Amino acid sequence: ASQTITVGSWGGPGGNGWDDGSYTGIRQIELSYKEAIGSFSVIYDLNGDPFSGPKHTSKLPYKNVKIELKFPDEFLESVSGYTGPFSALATPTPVVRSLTFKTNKGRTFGPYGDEEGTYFNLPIENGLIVGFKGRTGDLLDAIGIHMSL
Amino acid sequence: ASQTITVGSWGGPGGNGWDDGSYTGIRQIELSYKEAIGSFSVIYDLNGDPFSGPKHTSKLPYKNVKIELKFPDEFLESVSGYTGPFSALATPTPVVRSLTFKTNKGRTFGPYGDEEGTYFNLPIENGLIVGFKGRTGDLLDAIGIHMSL
Amino acid sequence: ASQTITVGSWGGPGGNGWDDGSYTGIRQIELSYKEAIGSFSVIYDLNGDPFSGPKHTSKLPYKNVKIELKFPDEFLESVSGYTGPFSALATPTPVVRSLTFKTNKGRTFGPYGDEEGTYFNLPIENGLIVGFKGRTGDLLDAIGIHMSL
Amino acid sequence: ASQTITVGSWGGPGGNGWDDGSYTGIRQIELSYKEAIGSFSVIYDLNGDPFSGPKHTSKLPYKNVKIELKFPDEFLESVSGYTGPFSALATPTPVVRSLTFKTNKGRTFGPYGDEEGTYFNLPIENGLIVGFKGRTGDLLDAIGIHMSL
Ligand SMILES: OC[C@H]1O[C@H](O[C@@H]2[C@H](O)[C@@H](OC[C@H]3O[C@H](O)[C@@H](O)[C@@H](O[C@H]4O[C@H](CO)[C@@H](O)[C@H](O)[C@@H]4O)[C@@H]3O)O[C@H](CO)[C@H]2O)[C@@H](O)[C@@H](O)[C@@H]1O
Ligand SMILES: OC[C@H]1O[C@H](O[C@@H]2[C@H](O)[C@@H](OC[C@H]3O[C@H](O)[C@@H](O)[C@@H](O[C@H]4O[C@H](CO)[C@@H](O)[C@H](O)[C@@H]4O)[C@@H]3O)O[C@H](CO)[C@H]2O)[C@@H](O)[C@@H](O)[C@@H]1O
Ligand SMILES: OC[C@H]1O[C@H](OC[C@H]2O[C@H](O)[C@@H](O)[C@@H](O[C@H]3O[C@H](CO)[C@@H](O)[C@H](O)[C@@H]3O)[C@@H]2O)[C@@H](O)[C@@H](O)[C@@H]1O
Ligand SMILES: OC[C@H]1O[C@H](OC[C@H]2O[C@H](O)[C@@H](O)[C@@H](O[C@H]3O[C@H](CO)[C@@H](O)[C@H](O)[C@@H]3O)[C@@H]2O)[C@@H](O)[C@@H](O)[C@@H]1O
Image (cartoon, rainbow over all chains, first blue to last red; front, side, top):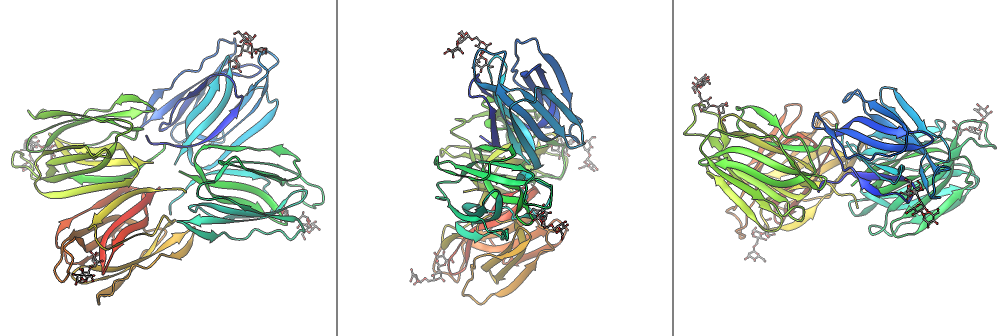
């Protein structure tokens, strides 16, 4: 067991809990969205070489986006997004409606989905997100992160 | 020069800047609140013994509070709070209007201040807050935190 | 880039430098030996599941040994071994003549090879070795480790 | 209660135990040596400012030394030293007979004491010493260290 500082758990209490674990760095991020984030997958770096992380896909006919990071010079500086219930869902729980990834080279990805509901921001001054935790039912219910130096 | 994962900078870019540093843990948090957050000091733990952190006191006549944590068994599990502009102030920049400290033993401190503006939540899953960064002018502009395992 | 505390670099200045990188934990260790450690490979744990690490095999007709750890309850508590030049080598540089892995459940592996030359001991009171660094020419020239909590 | 990777316990099980703790860095190390190591104090850095660490002084009449590190640019890169029994002592347990501090700027302190017994080397590749654990009776029995990034 190493263990990373894990802050997070942003969004719904529903869906199905999952945890990618901690790696070496973020190399790329995939995720479908529409009026909210559906699928979400990530490609971590593990000691200089790419490592395909576990998939958290969503049947929803959402929009796919590959976020290619200029790793390792570039890495996330902050993660933001919105959470809230969904018109289109049977369940009245909340979910990741939006998601915005900002990098240290001033690049910005998204916002994806809808910027509706309670906002959440994780400004990182020192350290790197090295892991993603979350819950996905029919779509990204919630999400959190792992960090190290 | 040891460093620590430092997430943060919730609040405005105004006031004068500061950073308490990284310690062993949090033993107690003192602060003054009214329609916003002013004074904010804290007593960190330094290898078992109490270390009085630098002062960040606001002239304003707010109501004071002592947050005595049942260290080392208890320690913050979360930090909520609000930020945004504010009347009664010549400056238009945003500041901490309210704070909320949840702890691992299920005890809740606050909300302190007016819950006005944009909410922010730092939910710690695994890890400890060990320091406070921030900005204070006439009162508490912003706030950030140092973390470690 | 995460990065782990890396202490080490025990043994010869020769051979060919290599680095396994940092993982999640030690799950098993393979290595050939005779009058010194020849081959050395390791199976790390990466978020609950086994991950075959890079191979550092040696042509030498040495003795093979698989060190199966009762992971995750069990993990190395200390690493010791000897370094020194080798009768059987052309080069007059030093190498990992011996190697002794001790676990937290009081189990002991080895010593492997020869307990000759300058001894080296890494007693760990808090933390886990999560990575191996080293140099291997015709046999394990040197070795070090990565650590986290 | 923050913790730190703590490797160590080089020396004997005798004398009375101690542990300075984890700080921000090492600024200066004081100590007394003759045919062995006696007194051993240290001034750690605490977020930019000097923090005088607890005293571990030995009655014996040894020669004293101030190890003034050119912090924060300079910090130890290695710790060598010897341990083993010792004459002039009723107790048969082992103790630190000598110490050697190498630094990142290529400066070397010591060897201090008699180089008698079993050598030990803590070569830091990546990381910082931030604390000292150990045991001291009439003089310095053993020594260990806290580390962090
Ligand atoms: O709200 C009424 C009713 O809801 C639950 O019963 C369900 C419901 O009848 C129906 O749900 C079908 C799916 O409808 C939408 O696609 C989603 O709400 C989906 O929920 C999943 O995804 C979201 C987001 O990822 C997540 O928050 C959820 O936890 C799920 O992972 C629904 O599954 O049909 C199913 C058939 O089994 C019913 O279970 C119950 O809560 C019920 O008590 C309630 O009255
Ligand atoms: O010492 C005399 C001579 O040595 C070097 O020349 C070599 C030498 O003539 C011969 O070496 C063959 C191999 O012999 C043994 O198997 C080993 O010493 C091996 O060395 C490798 O493994 C060890 C341990 O893993 C490691 O320390 C070494 O760095 C190597 O990885 C030898 O390779 O033939 C080769 C043919 O290329 C010669 O290079 C030179 O140092 C020479 O200056 C010296 O006079
Ligand atoms: O003389 C300079 C300044 O004086 C008068 O503004 C005065 C104070 O008015 C309010 O109380 C605040 O705006 C305060 O601002 C301080 O605190 C803020 C939060 O703590 C911070 O954002 C500010 O940077 C500052 O530290 C003012 O000090 C007024 O006449 C101004 O026009 C004039 O510039
Ligand atoms: O009264 C107890 C003890 O007294 C006499 O031993 C005395 C001192 O002798 C030597 O100086 C040392 O052995 C010293 O031992 C202390 O320091 C050691 C290293 O610092 C440590 O290992 C020991 O645990 C102890 O702290 C002794 O104090 C002698 O008459 C003994 O027979 C008698 O037990």
